[PDB]
Amino acid sequence: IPNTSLFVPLTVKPQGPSPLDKNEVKKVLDKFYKRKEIQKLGADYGLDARLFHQAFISFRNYIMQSHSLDVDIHIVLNDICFGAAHADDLFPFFLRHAKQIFPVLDCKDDLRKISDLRIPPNWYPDARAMQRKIIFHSGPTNSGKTYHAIQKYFSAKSGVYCGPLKLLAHEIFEKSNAAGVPCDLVTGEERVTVQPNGKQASHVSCTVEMCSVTTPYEVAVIDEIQMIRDPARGWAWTRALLGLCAEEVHLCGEPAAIDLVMELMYTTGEEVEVRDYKRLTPISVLDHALESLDNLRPGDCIVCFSKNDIYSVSRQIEIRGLESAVIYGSLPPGTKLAQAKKFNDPNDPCKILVATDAIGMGLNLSIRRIIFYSLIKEPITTSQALQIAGRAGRFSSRFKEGEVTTMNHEDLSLLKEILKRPVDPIRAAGLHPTAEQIEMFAYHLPDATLSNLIDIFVDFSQVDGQYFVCNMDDFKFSAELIQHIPLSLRVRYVFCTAPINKKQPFVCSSLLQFARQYSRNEPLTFAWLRRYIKWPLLPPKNIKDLMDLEAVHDVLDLYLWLSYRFMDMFPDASLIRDLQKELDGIIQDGVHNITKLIKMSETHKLLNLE
RNA sequence: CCGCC
């Protein structure tokens, strides 16, 4: 039943210069309002209580303040006043007014058919037209579960690697070419062709959002397939799984994902083969907390769940004469890699890593012991903890094997309770609105804002039981940010799907500026952006300075991502990429010397930690 | 707060 609270009223104003007794009409209208049958009638046409009331107020205001009323309606008013007409004889006119306020009502069925998201496999006739065999490589995080899949892909005549992260799409691109198997890179922000002339290699590595479902592939690898259930990003794994025209689809993920995949493949009638992988070296949950950093030991990783903690723990490590590496998600790619390369290096005294849950996926890290600094983000799910715990790995001179512990004593028994709790299997895969679907809604409801259309679409949508419609909060956020800029729905739609980090004012300001300039057909040149970011940029002096530089970096990424969809309007990507590699460079330095930034933050900006 | 496209 449509949630009528989503329908924003349209103003149907009264009309000016073009017998008629008002104290009478009032009495008629007010009875019109009260007849349990009129209400029950309205209800028939989908006007429940709230819509009835809102339509009625407008209608009654309409009738009462309009200089000239449409002729057919006067005639009907006179009869209920001074003839043998029943209230009911107004209802057809009421209904017309209502439908002008609430156009939804003229098209509930249309709206349902457009948002019918049932039997998603049918969205992919090319994949339906071929034999596809599924190979699920199930194992916990760090069980060499990917390894076999990758080789099969390297030796296939053609293949695609779908990754959960820019990082992993980069790693395989790098590992494939180094394996002498020419491989193109395809991500949102970056598209690299390796071939001399400029033709497509027969191997491609990409972030999952970007893979083609109309190219043939001998082999495809979809990595981290349990992400199919991620509230925001899930739709992308479902697309890859259902739609890749590969002769063998190799998935790699956790056992919790096997059931859903089986239900899915059943509806496609494709064969599935599970292959089990056990953990490389086993998982010993400790007995002694870290208690105090006076036990920090080469190979330790202290995992934090807020940046304040990152700066706090790393500070302490420096005051205690010990050297450390830092890793959090929003560090540029190069810096992350460089920070790990130090923590990994055997000839490097740096042997403590202070990190966020950013490490649970994407980086080659040689960690001996994981130390959960705390256990709260709500406590951390089994999946979450297991993912992270599972990073403890080598150092293989009798320190093979991995260890896990909390920071404090209060926390340790809880970590134990968590890690041996059974994992709920995943129940459904995500879907999302397509641009074309929303474009159709927008034809039906031209006066609804984009953000409101997403809500209405979602309310009207229908999915089979093994699926669910993805979160759209991010998209709705951008839609709200840019409602006041004139753009066709197609263009607006694309701008709203650009991945930005809402929590950063500069990124938001830039989304605005880019969209404004676009709408004004005024290209965003290399020269323009350099003025706008206020370049050149100096080394950071303190944390605020790093955050600001990370922000600018995020703005360059937003530009590049855009340059693939709007090429004339974003014409100088190569140049912007160059300037960004230069910025990742600046950040790397300021990050090497992070302890001094925390100092100038904690002694002058006194950023206290705890 | 984190994670991320």
Image: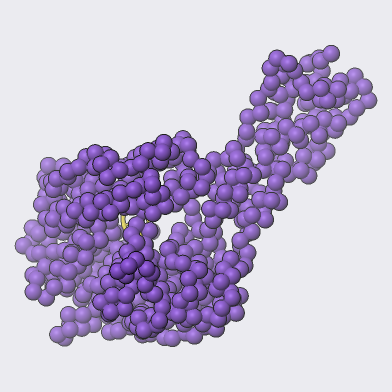
Q: Is residue A359 visible?
A: yes
Total marks drawn? 0
Give percent across and percent down for residue B3. Answer: 33, 60
Extreme-front residue of the structure: A197
Image location (x, y in percent) of residue A96: 75, 34
In the image, A260: left or right of A382?
right
Q: Is residue A474 left or right of residue A408?
A: right
What kind of colouring is applied to the model shown? Answer: by chain
Q: Is residue A493 above or below residue A225?
A: above
With respect to residue A210, does A13 lie above or below?
above
Query: Residue at position x 13%, y 55% from top?
Result: A589
Query: x, y (%) of residue A43?
Result: 76, 43
Note the chain letter of the purple one: A
In the image, residue A540 lies at what x, y percent?
15, 47
Task: Quadrant for residue A603, please give it.
Answer: top left
Is any part of residue A458 visible from this angle? no
| Residue located at (49% from left, 63% from top) | A235
- Compared to residue A113, the image places residue A488 above or below, namely above
Please state if A94 lies on the left or on the right of A376 as rendered.
right
Q: Give the camera-side residue of A577 and A290.
A: A577
Quadrant of the rendered image containing residue A510:
top left
Q: Residue at x 22, y 61 (%)?
A: A334
- On the picture, is A407 further left or further right than A149? left
**Residue sitting farthest toward the right:** A84
Q: Residue at x 20, y 45 (%)?
A: A544
